[PDB]
Length: 130
Ligand SMILES: *[C@@H]1O[C@H](CO)[C@@H](O[C@@H]2O[C@H](CO)[C@H](O)[C@H](O)[C@H]2O)[C@H](O)[C@H]1NC(C)=O
Ligand SMILES: *[C@@H]1O[C@H](CO)[C@@H](O[C@@H]2O[C@H](CO)[C@H](O)[C@H](O)[C@H]2O)[C@H](O)[C@H]1NC(C)=O
Image (cartoon, rainbow, N blue to C red):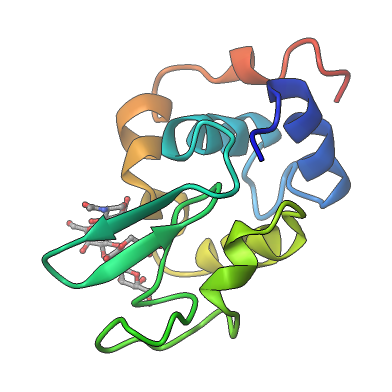
């Protein structure tokens, strides 16, 4: 489904995203908005490296989840990319959390760098009571 800004702010809050390894809730809100527009069913296919980005945080099938058709997939999140298209984002979160424990951290999402990095994200969580 498509969350509404403030439903997602509180929901991630409950899942422990605020301050998770130094990443403020607002930063996550920003990359979720630009990567998927708050949609858990979002899916983007890269014809070149035959990989697919899934769900709300647009996590890659070559490095994180398994869809059984991406050449050279390692499945670091030990998850089915399917888990990334269901309405409950519990596993989407458990995985984005694994993603940031890599050397590059939040730099793993280009939308973050383009529209979130150095563009003050205090705007996304203000009014949600988080
Ligand atoms: C987006 O794709 C990136 C490359 O396709 C990916 O970055 C790579 O992730 C690797 C994970 O084992 C490793 O950290 C490499 O150093 C890095 O280049 C990035 O993680 C992907 N982002 C998402 C959200 O899936
Ligand atoms: C999605 O974002 C990823 C990081 O924001 C990006 O992957 C990174 O690309 C770097 C290139 O200098 C380097 O290889 C990093 O190790 C890697 O994680 C990925 O390319 C972005 N998606 C697209 C389609 O560009």
